[PDB]
Each structure stands twice: as structure tokens, then as C-alpha cells.
Length: 194
Length: 263
Ligand SMILES: [Fe+3]
Ligand SMILES: [Fe+3]
Image 1 (cartoon, rainbow over the protein chains, first blue to last red):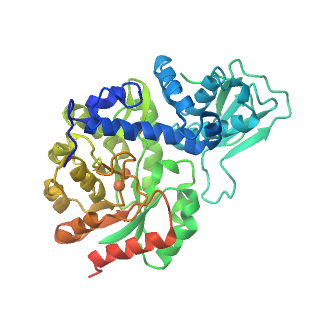
Image 2: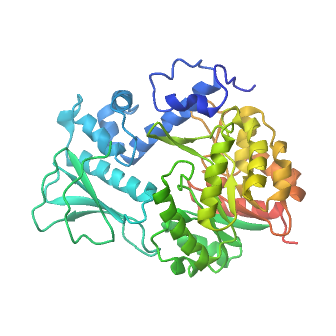
Image 3: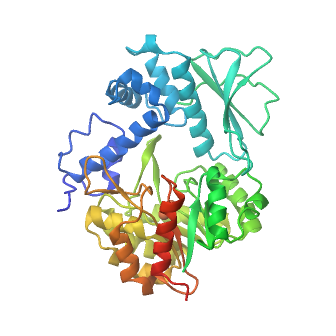
């Protein structure tokens, strides 16, 4: 009645393969270790595509044509699956068979996704807003601000227009952090983490 | 038994305040590290009831000490202002070899010496008694965890936040009976309860999705052993993290109060 743990016993035995859909097969279909990896791959799947559903217009409904190649490309380039996750998908997309079908309508949802992830998971006490820049978004940036009032009737992520010319970043994306909830100063873009 | 609700998203406020006013819950558990830049006095003035603290993302098992200390000191200032009923946190594997898990891992309970040292240090930073929650086990570490939390709790003064749902997941995925936790249930006064889901490819494996009504066996568990759960200072926080529906929540709440009548 229980699913056999089969080759392994505890979650720690599965750590290395929790984000590697290639190595999922090496576990028996009916095995519990196969099931647990699937739960964890579904979590990466849904984080990507629930938050950015327009990317399924590129991959098709199964998301396979993006997900598998991006997952394997992520282990290879040892990304941390940090808040830059979404931006790192768009970067992969820029060099995939989909590179001609990227437009602002795909770009902005992944910037809002990374901005929201940062303001949700980040635990740096002296970091209050994130400021995302891309080379495909001149003069503007996507700013993600942590919650600082239970009554803010606005969204925590905003596209903001600068008045002074804003340098294009070196890579496709660049970012910086602000110590309070103001932008008084441009320290220059930092490259995407990892 | 005080019944509670977990407050996580800023946009649930008007609904949570209404369950307070309507005496459907007696306190509010807060995912406090999501509100660390809010003014703390503001949270205390939005809830006409006690609060308790749940910490999701300290990552005290892996976080660098300088970032961890700064979080601790900010949490300390919040503890002073709100006097939370309790302060709780998790035992979670977040990061393998530098990369982040999106479905968090059950720590390897054979690593007792490493958990103990971080739990002591973190609880020192927080300046108060910490409660640690049990993982909703999938792999067979479920058989190890009851004996592990018991040990950890007497060598470090730490409490157990016993989540009934997660223990029933553990039972269904591994066979490990919730009865393994009787001594902890009879000791701690703070509990969690939620609904659990299923994997997309295996309905037999149970997930801590916190999205639906509780199972008929998570309610049998609280019923069968209501004497062991209920005790003088006891509380149970109902978690619903997805499909936050005011009426579906409200019946699960009354369902709880049926099991634990006020006197
Ligand atoms: Fe929890
Ligand atoms: Fe819980």
C-alpha cells in the first residue's frame, strides 16, 4: 500500500536530484523517491509558469520546450535559483528557438516576477527596494519594495520612469538595492546574481 | 483551546479582523518575517486579540551570522512591542550546494549535532523560548523525527509547535503513526492544523498545500486524542495559505471549536 522508498530512505538522499528532470528517470516509476522529485519539479514548474503564464504561449501548454532545456542549462551554469530565477529564464530564452518571439509583453511579467520574489524571500534588514533594469527597457525600471505599512493600497512592484538618462546595463539585466523606500541616488547596475 | 488563524498576505486584513470581532478566532499567528519593515505598533493596533509569531525564512540552519543577527535584533524589537503568545520557526533544508530548493527538504535527522548548535544560537538571538515545527515528511525520516524533536527539546529548552496535519501527512507517506508524537502532544501547548493535498501523479502521497479543508483523519486525530491536545494554555492555529475563502475557512473553524468546546 505504501510506495517503496526503493534505492534510498530519507529526503537527504534525494537532495542532488530535486531540480534535475533528466536524472528523475533513474528512480523506479512506482518508487516513492520518484514521487518526491516530481513534487519538487512541479514546484519549479509552477513557480515559473503560474507567475508568468504568457511564457506558455512560447512553450505550449506543457511548458516542456522551455522547462527541460532551461533546467538542464541551469545545473550546467550552476544558477542558485535565487530571486533572479525568472530573469535567468528570459536570458536563456534570448538564446533559444524562441528568441525572435520576445517582446515587452513577455519581458515585463518576468521582471515583475523577480521583483516580487525578492521582496518576498529576501531577509536583508538594510535592503528595502530592489531596482531592476534591462537593456530592453530604456529610461524605466521595475522597482520592488518590501511592505512598510499594512495599509498600502498600491502594489509593491511598480514600473517607474526616470528623468535623468539611465545607463543600459551591461548584460540583459542589472539591478541594485536601496537602503530606504526612496531612490535618491543611482550607484550603477550590478549584474544578475549567479 | 484557543483557536487561531495564520495571517500571511497583507490583503486578508479586513477578513481576519472580522473573524476576531465575531469571536471565531482568539488570536492571530503572524508570518512575522514578512512584516519586518512595517512599524510594529501598527500590527498590534490592527488586531484586538493576542498575536503569536511564526518565522518562515530565518534559514537559521544555513544563514550567515551577520544577516541572521540583524534579523534576530529586528525580531527582538517586535517581541518587545507585541508580546507574542509564542515565537516559532521551522527545521528546513533550503539550499543544496548553493542552489535553492523550491519544495523545501526534510533535514536529515542524523545530523543532530549540527541542528542543536544552530537552534541554540538562533534561540539565543531571539531572546526567548523558541518552538520548532515538525516537517510533513515524505521520505522515511518521519520515523526518526519524534525521537529527534524530543531530544532537541530537552537539551536546548526549545518547544515543539506540533502541526497535526504534517504529522498525518507523515503517516500517510511513510506509515509512521502520529501516535509516535503522543509525548510531545501532551507536553506542548501550541498546535497547527490545515488541509493537505495530493501530488499530481500520485494521490497516495500527501502534500502540505494548506489549500483545502482538513481531512477526515486530521479531524479524527484531534477528536481521538482531544484530551492529550487540550490543556490549560493550549492553542491551535488553523492555516489556510491558498484559496482563502471566508466561508470555507469559517466552517473549518467551527469544526475546530466543535472538537474543543470553550469549557
Ligand atoms: Fe510552518
Ligand atoms: Fe503549520
